[PDB]
Length: 115
Image 1 (cartoon, rainbow, N blue to C red):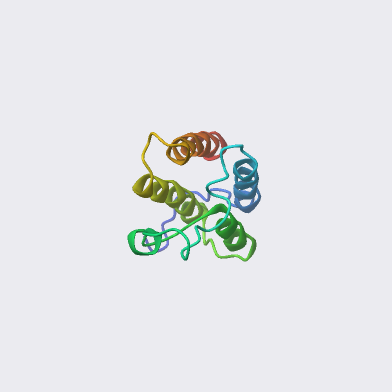
Image 2 (image 1 turned 90 degrees about the vertical axis):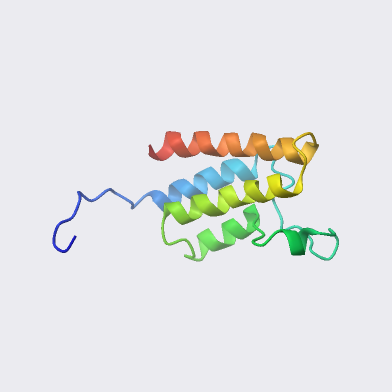
C-alpha cells in the first residue's frame, strides 16, 4: 500500500532472458506449426473460432518493440499459442502433439529461469 513496498525484485535482465527462451523455442524442431500466423484466408474455421490468434513471430515483434509491459504478459502470449493449438487440434495429431511438447518445453525453461 501507499509508502509500504515489498522488497524490489530485479527485473533488469528479464527482456534478455525472455528473448533467450523465445530463441530456444523458435529453434525447436516441433516449432513449425507456431512460427508464423495461421493464414486466415486458407484455414477454414480459424478466424471465427480462435478469438485471439498468436504465434512466435508476433511474440518476437512485440518483445522487440517494447509491447510487453512485464514478464507475465509475455508468458500469457506464449501460453495463448498453445491454448489456441489445443482448441483447434486433436491431441492425436502431429500439430496437437507439437503443441503439448512445446508447452512442456516452455514451462520448464520458465520455471528454471525465474522461480
